[PDB]
Length: 224
RNA sequence: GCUGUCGUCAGCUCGUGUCGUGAGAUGUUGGGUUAAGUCCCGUAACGAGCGCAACCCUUGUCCUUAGUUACCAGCACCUCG
Ligand SMILES: [Mg+2]
Ligand SMILES: [Mg+2]
Ligand SMILES: [Mg+2]
Ligand SMILES: [Mg+2]
Ligand SMILES: [Mg+2]
Ligand SMILES: [Mg+2]
Ligand SMILES: [Mg+2]
Image (cartoon, rainbow, N blue to C red; front, side):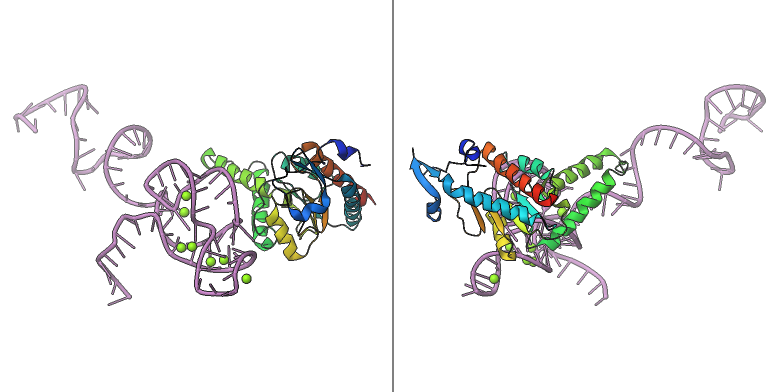
């Protein structure tokens, strides 16, 4: 907010100068010490416009999926999905999570039934030779599928933190014609992102800044 | 219909999705591990099916039920079986 909060945490940084997508050239303020620098004066209006978009979309009882699976990122994405609701993914994105959603509905149902019978009084009362490995199966399933337990329909908008890390996901969205909100860095390509946010990745302070901005926007939009 | 053979070898496929103009590919590739496509970890693939394993018969130890035509530890007789 107000050109200073992001000025300190991590935003004005880029993946060196050897690696850089030329299509991002319009968002480069300059290069210092063989590191690309992003022009904040251009990304503030885009960030505010995206916040307005998300706030207005959250008024209308509709879902925005959060995608942030990466080092030290999927965690805070999880706790930001905590409160304000909304779906999320924090571990590996399974190919076909959108274009092949009918098949993954079955795994959703299997997880829901297994978790129902797991905490129904601990129905896993049989011998531990099978109980521990069934619990391991539950753990592995909830690890990569826990976020979209709810949200039975297709999400309306997708929010991704890193863009080239999540390219598969973006492609699926671009096939179903749903908007994409992304934090595009220097190396990534802004192609396939409807609301490009030229920010920074890998910076915990920066990424939590985006997550809290999004959380407050969606909370205000849903409040009415 | 029934049978041999590869071969009791660990393999052979399908649905949806994705890649290629197409035949096709992916799943089923990779690091380990196993008798085993057995299992774990990663992974544009997510699942399922037939195989593998388990369920079956027998043998190896123990308990309850029962002691005839089977048995004889203890008692009595014994022509000494
Ligand atoms: Mg095959
Ligand atoms: Mg097939
Ligand atoms: Mg197929
Ligand atoms: Mg095609
Ligand atoms: Mg093949
Ligand atoms: Mg292998
Ligand atoms: Mg098997």
